[PDB]
Structures are given as structure tokens and as C-alpha cells.
Amino acid sequence: HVGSFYNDNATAKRIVDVIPEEMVTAGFKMSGVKDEKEFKSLWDSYKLDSSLVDLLCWARLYGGAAMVAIIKDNRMLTSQAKPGAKLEGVRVYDRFAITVEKRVTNARSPRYGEPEIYKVSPGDNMQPYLIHHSRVFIADGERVAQQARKQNQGWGASVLNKSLIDAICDYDYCESLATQILRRKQQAVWKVKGLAEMCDDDDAQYAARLRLAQVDDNSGVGRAIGIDAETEEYDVLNSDISGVPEFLSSKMDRIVSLSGIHEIIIKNKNVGGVSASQNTALETFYKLVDRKREEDYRPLLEFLLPFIVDEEEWSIEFEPLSVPSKKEESEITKNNVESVTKAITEQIIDLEEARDTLRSIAPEFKLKDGNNIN
Amino acid sequence: HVGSFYNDNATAKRIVDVIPEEMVTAGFKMSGVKDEKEFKSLWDSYKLDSSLVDLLCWARLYGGAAMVAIIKDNRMLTSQAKPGAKLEGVRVYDRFAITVEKRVTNARSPRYGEPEIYKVSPGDNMQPYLIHHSRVFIADGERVAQQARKQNQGWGASVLNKSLIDAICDYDYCESLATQILRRKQQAVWKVKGLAEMCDDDDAQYAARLRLAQVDDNSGVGRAIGIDAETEEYDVLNSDISGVPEFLSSKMDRIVSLSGIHEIIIKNKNVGGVSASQNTALETFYKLVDRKREEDYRPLLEFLLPFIVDEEEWSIEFEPLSVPSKKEESEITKNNVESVTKAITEQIIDLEEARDTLRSIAPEFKLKDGNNIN
Amino acid sequence: HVGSFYNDNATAKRIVDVIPEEMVTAGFKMSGVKDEKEFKSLWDSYKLDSSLVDLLCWARLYGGAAMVAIIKDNRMLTSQAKPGAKLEGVRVYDRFAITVEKRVTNARSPRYGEPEIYKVSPGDNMQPYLIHHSRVFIADGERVAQQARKQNQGWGASVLNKSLIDAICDYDYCESLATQILRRKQQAVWKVKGLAEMCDDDDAQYAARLRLAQVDDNSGVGRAIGIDAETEEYDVLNSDISGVPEFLSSKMDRIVSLSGIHEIIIKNKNVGGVSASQNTALETFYKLVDRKREEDYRPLLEFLLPFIVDEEEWSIEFEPLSVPSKKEESEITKNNVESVTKAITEQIIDLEEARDTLRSIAPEFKLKDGNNIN
Amino acid sequence: HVGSFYNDNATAKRIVDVIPEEMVTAGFKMSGVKDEKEFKSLWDSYKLDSSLVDLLCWARLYGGAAMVAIIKDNRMLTSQAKPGAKLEGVRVYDRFAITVEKRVTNARSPRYGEPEIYKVSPGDNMQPYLIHHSRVFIADGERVAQQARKQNQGWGASVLNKSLIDAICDYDYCESLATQILRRKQQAVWKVKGLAEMCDDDDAQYAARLRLAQVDDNSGVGRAIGIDAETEEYDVLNSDISGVPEFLSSKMDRIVSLSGIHEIIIKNKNVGGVSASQNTALETFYKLVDRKREEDYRPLLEFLLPFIVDEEEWSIEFEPLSVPSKKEESEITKNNVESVTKAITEQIIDLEEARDTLRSIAPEFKLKDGNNIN
């Protein structure tokens, strides 16, 4: 069961939860709507951030998840949701809590074989309640071969496959072995002529062990032991610890290679390379996050938006993860403003187009609505 | 069977799926159409991203795949599809699910010997349904010699050839051996005078083994063992771990060399080289992705587009993989604007051509349709 | 046979197919034609990319190949192809599928001894069909001495000569030896007094081997073995792994030296040298690719074009392999525009010549046809 | 025989063929002709590239070669070729296929003792046909002392002298020895008390060898062997591999020194030195190629041209091997244009001379014929 491994291990938890939070925190930007501040207020009214993050995390962990949208359509759950309603809230679920009841049986239809009505078992104390497929969004995990997908009742695979679990367990075992190797570096062996002639439970053994304990407690550098010759000796056996840290670093490097995430994120320790600018070492992680958002986050937004946004025409543009410093921002604004001003001269751009370009390219300027100036 | 190896190993999965996602995520740009935003909305309506990615992944994994386009031509599946239909959806398949029924028998025809009607077995519960070759696109994998291609019923080879599988198994075995070598670094051997005079199952062996377990549990540095002389000894044997990490790194380097992908992608660890600018290390991977997109992604788009785009004349231009930073973009726009403005002076370029040049070269400017200005 | 070696080995496959794809992907540019977009559409209609790449790959692999052009001359295959037809398609073939029937017997003719009619055996199920030499293009492989060329029935040699195969096999053997050397680093030898007085198949040997297996399974650091003195000993023999990775790297360096391709392409691992600009390390590979285009790719285009391009006058100019970044492109355009503008002043360049220079030097500008401006 | 060595060895093949291809690919430029595009079309009509490359390669390999020019002179082969004919094609030959029949016997003539008529044996099935010396070009190989030249029937020496062959064979033998040294690093010797008391062919030897094979197959780290004491032992003998790669690199360095070609070309591996600009390391090779072209390629062109070019006055200028990048080209053009413009001012250069200077210095400008402007 992956739940216990996710709970106990911190590395697995970071691997599972590092991507969805990074994707969701950046946010999204929509163009084509008339009122932008009103839309922002409407979106922040629903406060669906935690539900989205939990849905993505469960989809990555278990291999599947789903979200049920509660709507004010004034009809049955089985009945289709007509356009026009404005949503009341969402309910995230787990992979094992949803099963299909009926599916399409029309061969000529392009949507043939896909589910039509889901049971949606809520667990806890409630009873299952069927829902039309137009009100349920199915999020799939990692891609799996179709033959194994059929055995997985049409659900994807999990991020924590066999290789990652084996690597993490191997690293933990190697760390334990390293501690044990450090523990036994010197051993002092004490030999006596007659020592097997004891009852093994009488006062003689007790006294001998107490004496040995006190002697090894009080000895060291600057203190000596008096040994009786011709009946007793004292020897010390040494060892070494040569290349343990490099071994552990190599095993952690294997974990980093298998996980699919940059070493800076997993090891959470810079200085591994020379001091670069900043984002240069994180460009690979940023590319991975952009690919992941384009693959997973966009369908969820395109499913949720038609039930919130009134306008029929809209599009989603994702904000960049990497933002420049304030000085670079000022230089960029100055360059854009000078370019627009040069465009204004020689009369090739007109005032209205230049004003729109200034409004869009440079959001720092607080332009007033309308191109009528004074 | 390559399915189990693909499922279990993370490295093989990354090798298979790293390229198609990189190709598809970047996207494509078409020129020559009248409406750009309308075409974008129409393309995003079909949401064929997952089908394309799965088709390319299956083509790289199994060696072959195909996609069936469901079209609204209003006739039999065997009949040819006339221009004018506007598509309803797609359906990807696997290599083993499609076989040929009849082929061309006209010697003088240039398309002689090619398939004409495919069986298209859908598996599951449905029955095979023949389809004309004009509605089926065949995606081929890696290039194979013709003699072996005939034995492969006219299908390509797989990315996971024998060498890659051997290298991956060898690396896993070497890592296991490295762990075993770390495990046995010190051995403590205990000798007794009379030890073979035991019943091998009586209480004496139990007591001796319990004593040995307790003694090796409680020993270490700062603790001593009392040994009876002239009947018993205690020795420790050591070993070393000198060049294991370099050996493992060399084996991983062989895997990287055989795979055909840059070490940054596979090892997923920068710092291997000195801190460069950014894309300088990834130029080889970008060139590989560009070659792969030109070889594979373009035919799929040229097959899908005629059933979507109404205009007869069009062309596909692929977006670059590497994009500059915002400051560099501002400088580029400034330079282009300055050049266009200098072209306007001395009256060698005319206002209209400069306006189209500004519209094309610099997408940031929101020029208004028409060259009539005010 | 080279087919099995090409199929099994990934390094040989990369060596064979790295050049032709690089040459074909870059493309070609033609000057002197009236309509450029119409020519581009006509060329992309035939989609002869795969056939060209396969022809070049087979020529490099086997030593020879040929391509047959299907023309609309409306005469016999033996009869000459009259200029004016506009092609239907091509069929690529293999070296062993073509043999000569009749050749020139006129001593005074400069084309004396060359083939006249080829049999062209299509294999599969079809029958041989003779073709005039004006419709068949013969692609030759690596250059060979004439004496060996005669024994090779007038065909070139292969890229995979004896030295390359020997080097690859030697490298594989050395890697196997390296794995075997890592495998045997420590050995534990167990000695018993009365060990040869056994029936070799009875219960005693079974019990002894089970005991040995369990003991070596449960031993390690922190675990001890009890040994009976005066009748049994336990020893450990060690070894070392000092310079294996350097040996393997040297063998791979020999393979790189013999192959004739840059180490970045074959080893597919940067960081080998210090971080350079980019193309600086790849200039040698680019020069080799350019020479290969000028040697092999140009004759194929000069053979195919007369059956496509209507105009009698044309020339082929190859696009550069290395392209600058966008910022460098903007700077280049700015410099060129400044130079043209300075040429306009002082009235030494004329308006029409300057407009043509701007049209050719800077494709980015979308100049309108005609020099009449407004 | 040098043919087998050239065929089998890749290094010898590269040494022989690296120079002629580099010389021919760059091309030549002629000045003084009226029509340049017509001359280019005429030159590309004959397509004599492969013949030139083969002639130079054979001259470097065997020590001598020749080229026979087929001319439309409408007289006997023995008769001299009058000026005016326009060539039909060429035929390259080999050193052993040509022998002299008659030579000059006039002492006072400066061309005394030189050949007059060559036999020209075509080999194959044709018969020898004498040709006047005005239609045969003789290409000589490496310079040789006159005493040895007389014994070589007036032909030069070969590039592959004794030293290069010895060095290559020594390097191959050293590589084989290195592989053999890696092979035998550890040896395990097994001793038994009674082992010579066997029939050497009975079942006992078979059983012993099978047991030994299985034991050495199943042993390693983590597995032990049970040895019977007082009748049998087990020992392992080690070795080392200390400085083999440096030895091999030194031998390859000797090969590079003897060959006469830069180490970058032969070793085909950069990174040997620190990252330079680009051509800085290749300047020596470029100087060698310029010397070789000036020594060998020019006479061939000066022999072929009078039978193609109609104009009596012409000269050949060789294009440089090293070309600057596009940005450097733009800067060069800007500097040249500004210099010409400054020359125009103060009226010291006149318009016509400046226009000619712009036409020649900067070929990017498409100047119109005539200096009449408008």
C-alpha cells in the first residue's frame, strides 16, 4: 500500500507534492473577458485552491482521482447540465470511490465505449448517488501500457513505481550500514588465563564484569591500565572509514536520476555547482513544470471555466514561472516605452493602437479607459 | 515482451516518452489562413493532444501504430472520403490490432503493392470493421533492414533494442553488487577450542548463539570483550571500497551513449559541467528534437489538417524550442522597430509594406486591421 | 552479413544513419525560378523525403543503391524519357536487386562501357522489368580500389569496414571483462578437516551446502561466525579495481577515431571539454556534413529536378547548417539595412537595385512585387 | 601491395583521401571572362568532380595517374589537337595502364627526352590506342630522388611509405597487447593432492572439469567455496594495469607526427586543447591544403580550361577555405561600404570606379549592369 510509504517517507512526499503546488501557485491569466477585476473577485470567491492541489496530488499518488461539480441546474443528477448555471462548489474524490455503471453502446458515435453514468460512492456514512458524466472530471496519472491499463480498470499508474521504492529502501539501508561501520572502529579485547571456570551466574562473573566496565569507563589518553604478566593480555584492533560519503552520495545520485526531478530540489542543497546567475540551474525544472501544467492543469480549468465565466469566448494563458528582478523590469519597461514612442513618430502606428500596446505590454502604467485623451 | 520492461523500469519509460512530449508541447504555427484566432479555437475544440502523444509513444515503443479518423462523409467506411467533411474525432490503435486485407494489383500504377483496405480489429468487445486506406494513418518506428522488415510484417523496429536492454540490466546488476560490497566490509571471526561436539539442535547451541548475538550487539568502541586464553580467540577481517562510484558512473555513461539522448536529460543532474549560459548544453537535444519533429510530427498534421482547415492553401511552420528571456525580447523588438523606421525614411519601403513587416516581425504590437490609418 | 550487425548494434546504426538525416533535414534552396511558393508546394506534394533518406542510408550501409523514377512519357520503359513529363513518384531499391543487361559498344563515344539497360529485379512477387538508363539513378558508396571494385561487380564499399567491426567487438568484450572484474572483488574460502569423506550425493552434502548458504546469507558487518578451532578456518581474499574506467574510455576513443565522426555525436555526452560558445566544437562535424552534401546530395537533386521544374534555367544553393540566434539575426538585419540606406545616399546605388538587395539580403522584410512604390 | 592496406585500414584511407576532397570541395574562381553565369553552367554541365577527385586520390595512393581528354577535333588520336574544340568528356586511368612509345630525339629542343606518344592501355576488354601527348595529363605523386625515380620508370613515390605502415602496424599490435593485458588481471589456481593419477580421457577428468566450471561460474562476492583441508588449496594471483592509455596515446601521437596531418583531423576528437575560437587550431591544416592546391590542383585546371573557355585571356583565383560568420560578414560589408562612400566624397574616386569597387568587393549587392544609373 502506497499510503504508508507516502506518510512515513519524506522524500516520497516531496516527490509527490513538489509539482502540483508549483503549478498551482503560479496561477493563470485569461484574455478576451470584458471585466478582469470582476472575474478575479468571482474566482477568489470560490477559493478552490486546496481542492485543485489535493486532486492533483491524489492523481499523482494513487494513479487516479475525480472531481464532482455541484451545480444549481434545478434538475436530477442523472440529467445533463444545461449551459447557464453558475456553480456552487466542488467535491474531490479518490480513485477507489468511483465506478462506472453504464457506457455508450452506439458503434457509429465517435464517443463509443466511454462511460456515461458514474456511481460515485462517497464513503463515510452517505450512500452512492449516480451522476451524469457531464458533471464529473476524471484525472489520470502516469501513462501505462494498454494491457496493464485494462487490468487496472481503466486507471493510470502511480509515480512511485518499483524502481523508486527500491532505490529509497536501498539508500536507507546503506545509511544504516554507514552508521554501523562508524560505530565499530576500535575493539579492545581482554584475555585472561582462567576465565571459563565460572558458574556463569554467580558473584564471580558479576564482579569481573563490573571491574571491566569501570576500567573501560575510566581509561583513555593520560590514563593507564596495570596488567598482570604471564596470565593476561590487552589488545586493540583498529579499522578504517575511507569512502563512505562518496558511496552515499552515489546512491543519492541514483535516486535523483530515477525520480525525474532536479538535484537542487531533491537534495535541497546548492553549492553543488559553481555560483551561477540563478535560474540557469533551474531551467530544466521550469521546463518540466511548464510541460506538466500544459498537460494536466489546462483541462481542469477548461472544464471549470464555462460554469463560471458568462462570456462564450475566452482563452487561458499561463503566467511564466521565472520573473526578472525589479531593475530588469524597469529596463524592460523603458525599452518598450521608447520603442512605442519611436513607432508613434513618422505616423505608422496611430494613437489608439499605441495606447492599446502600452496598456498590454506595460501593465505598470495605469491607463484610463478610452482612447479619447483630452 | 517490452510492455513489462517499459512498465517496471523508469529509465526506459523516460527514454520512450521524453521526445514525443517535447515535440507536441511546443506546438505548430500555420500561415496563409485568413482567420487565425478562429482556427485556434477550432483546433482547441477537438483537443487531440493526448491522442497524438499516445500515438507517438506507441509508435516508438511497439514499433508501429495507427490512427483512425471518424469522418462525417455520409457513406460506407470502405468508400473513399471526399474533400469537404469536417471531422468528428480520432481513434488511436496498437500495432497488433490492424492487418491488411487487399492491396493494389496494378503494376503500372506508382502506388503498387501498398495496402488498400485495413481490417482494423478494435479488440475488447467490438468486431473488426474494414476501413478505406484514405482514412487510416500508419505511423512507423525506427528504421529496419528490408529483410527483417519483411519478417516484421511490414512494421518498423523498436527504440528498445537488445543493446539498451543489456546495458540497463548490467547497470542494475552492478548497483546490486556495489550494495553487497558495502555490506561486507568487516567480519569478526570467533574461534573456540571445542565447538563441533554439539547436538546441533539442543540447548547448548541455542545458548551459544544467544550469547554471541548479545555480545555482538553490545560491543563497539568503548566496550570490551573478555576472552578466555588458551581456548578461544577473536579476529577481525577488513576490506576496502576504492573505486565503486567511478565504475557505476562509467556504466551510466555507457547507458547514456547507447540511448541516444543527452546526459542532462537522462541523469537529470546538472553541475556535471561548468556553469554555462543555459541552452548551450541543450543545443544537441534541441537539434535532435527538431529533426524528430520534422521527420514524424509533420506528416500527422498534414494528414489531419485537410479535414479541418477550409482553405485549400496553407503551410505549417514549427515554433522554435528555445525562447529568449524578456529583456532579450525587448531588445530584439527595439532593434526591429528601429530598422523598420529607418527603412521608412528615404522612401524605399512604403507605409503598407512596413506595416505588414511590423505586424509579422513583432507580434507584440497590436496593429489594427487595414493600412488606411487615420 | 552486415544486416544483423546493423540491426543489433546501436552504435553502428547511429554511424550509418547520422549523416543522411542531417543532410536531408537542412534542405535546399533554388534560385532563378519565377514562382518560389508554387515550386515549394509542388515539391512538398511529392513528399519524397523518406525515399531519399532510405536511399542514402542503403547506399552507406550495403555499398550501393538505386532509385527508379516513374515518368509520364507514354512510351515503353526501354524507350528514352523525353523532356517535358512531370513525374508520378519514385521507387527506391537495393544493391542486389539490379543487374545490367546491355552496355555501350561504341569505342569513339565518350560514354563507352557504361550500362544502357538495367534489369531491375523487384523481388517479392513481381517479375523483372527492363528500364532505360535515363530513368535510373545509381548511388555509390565509399570509394574502393579499382581491382576490388571489379570483384564487387562495379559497386562501392561499405562504411562498416573490418576495422570498425573489430573495434566495436573489442569494446563490447572489454565491457564484459570489466563487469566480470567488478563481480569478483572478495572471496571467502572455508576449510574443513574431514570434508572429502562424503558420498557427493547424500544428505550430508545437502545439509552442509544449506548451512553454508544460510551462514553467508546472514553474515556481514555487525554479525560474527563461530568457528571451531584446530579443525576449521575461514579466510577472505581481496582484489582491486584501479584503472578500468580509463581503459574503457580509451577503447571508446579508439572507436571514435576510427569511425570518422566527432566524439560529441557518438559519445552523446558534452562536458568532455570546457563550456564553449556552441558551434565551435561542432564545426568539424558541420564541415564533414557540408562536404557530404556537396558530394552525394547534389547529383540526386540535379537528377530529380528536370522532371519537376518547368523552367530550363535553375541552380541549387544549399542552406547553411548553423543558424544564429534571434538577437544576432536582428543585429545582422540592422547592419544590412544601415548599409543599404547609406548606399542610397550620394546616389550610387539606385532605388531599384537597393530594393532588390533588400529583398534578397533580408528575407524578413515583406516587400511588395514591383519597384514602382507610390 | 598498397591496395589491400588501403582497403582494410581506415586510418590509411583517411590519410589518402582527406586532402583531395578538401581541395576540390572549396572550388575555384576565374576572373577576366565576360559571362560568369554562362561559364558556371558550362562547367557544371560536364560534372567532372568525381573524375578529378579519383585522379588526385590515385596519384596520392599509387604514385602516378593520368587523365585522357576526349576531344571533338575530327582527326586522328596521334595527330595534335588544334585550338577551338570544346571537349566531350574525360577518362581517368591508373599508373600501370600507361606506357610511353616514342620520345623527343632533338637535342637542341628545350623539350628534349620528354614523351611524345603514350600507349594508353585501357585494360578490361578494349585494346591499346596511342594518343598524342597534347591530350594526356600526367599527375605525379610524392617527390623522390632521381636515382630511385629511374628505377620507378619515371613515376613518383607513394604517400604510404615504410614508416607510416610500420607505425600503423605497431599501433594495432600495441592495442591487441593492451586488450590481452586487461584480459589477464586475476588468476585463481586450484591445487589437489592427487591429480596426476588419471587416465586423462576417462570419466574422472570430465567430472572434475565440470565441477570446476560450475564452481567458478557460481562463485563471487557473497558466495563461498568449501575447501577440504590438508589435501587442497585455493589461491588468487593479481596484476595491475597502470599506464596503458598513456602508452597508446604516445603511439598514436607518433602516427600523427609521421603522417603529416593535424591531430584534430586524424584523431577526430577535439577537447585535446582548451576551447579556442575555431580556425586557430586548424590554421596549420589550412596552410597545408593551400600549399597542396597551389602545387597540384592548378595545373589540372590550366590544362582543362583552354578546351572549355572560349576567351584567350583568363586567370584562376582560389577561394579561401576559412569563411567568417554571418555577423562578421555584415560588419565587413558595412566597413567596405562606408570606406567607398568616404572615397566618393571630396571627388577623388569618381562614380564609375566606386561602382566597380562595390560590385567586386561586396558581392551581396546586386548591382545592375552599366554605370549610367538614372
Image (tube, coloured by chain):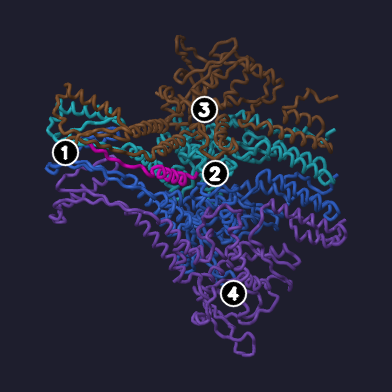
Chain colours: A brown, B cyan, C blue, D purple
Instruction: Find disc 4 in the rendering and name its residue.
Output: D68
Residue B298 point in image, percent of width and height:
59, 41
- Helix, strand or loop for disc 3: helix
- Helix, strand or loop for disc 1: loop
**Which amino acid type is shown beneath numbered disc 2?**
Val
- In this rendering, do the residues under marks 4 and 2 share a single chain? no
**On what subunit does the disc labeled 4 rest?**
D
- Helix, strand or loop for disc 2: loop
Comparing B364 with D171, the one in front is D171
Q: Is residue C187 above or below residue C169?
A: above
Q: Residue at x 50, y 23 (%)?
A: A57
Q: Are marks 1 and 2 in contact (CB under 8 Å)?
A: no
Instruction: Find disc 2 in the rendering and name its residue.
Output: B274
Mark 1 Cα-neighbour bin, 10 Å: few <14, some 14–19, many ≥20: some
Alpha-carbon distance for marks 4 and 1? 94 Å
Task: Indicate which disc residue A18 carries.
Answer: 3
**Which amino acid type is shown beneath numbered disc 4?**
Val
Q: Is residue D88 visible?
A: no
Mark nearest the camera among 3 and 1 is 1
Instruction: Find disc 1 in the rendering and name its residue.
Output: C229
**Which amino acid type is shown beneath numbered disc 3?**
Val
Alpha-carbon distance for marks 1 and 2? 59 Å
Magenta residues? Answer: B234-261
Mark nearest the camera among 1 and 2 is 1
Q: Are marks 3 and 2 in contact (CB under 8 Å)?
A: no
